[PDB]
Image 1 (tube, each protein chain N blue to C red):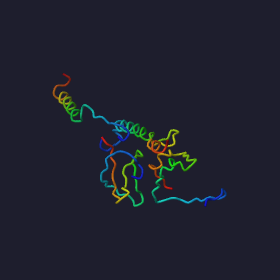
Image 2: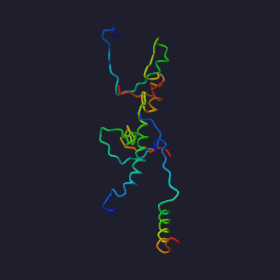
Image 3: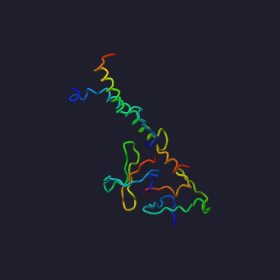
Length: 49
Length: 34
Length: 49
Length: 49
């Protein structure tokens, strides 16, 4: 992406980001979801098994 | 889980605990302490 | 009594809550810098020589 | 034209591709010294500015 380099499984998200947010986190301060820099689809990030 | 934290299952599931409890009640009710 | 008084089962609820906190603490301590320039290992690896 | 050191050009670089052309390997410079970043990782890193 634009940073937030990492490894995981990218799936469609049901999250509703406010138009300015771009990124998102969990309770654990980990990345929860990322807005795709192009087309702006929100994707959830799941750790690999 | 993102940092390696794994939760393990119990050997005895709630269903098995319920069966042991039921057996103890059946014993208590129909045969006392014998 | 068990239905109307939620505190009745407090002993079992407490065991659950203490272990949940021990894990949440472990998770949050992970994001502290501990004297490092960044708590994110990937930031250190990505920019520092 | 370059300023004498009294003043200096402070042009801000934004909304672009900072291809750093591995300038450190061009041998056109006598000095190319990076501090908070590794000079070889400059093309992987993003900046706000």
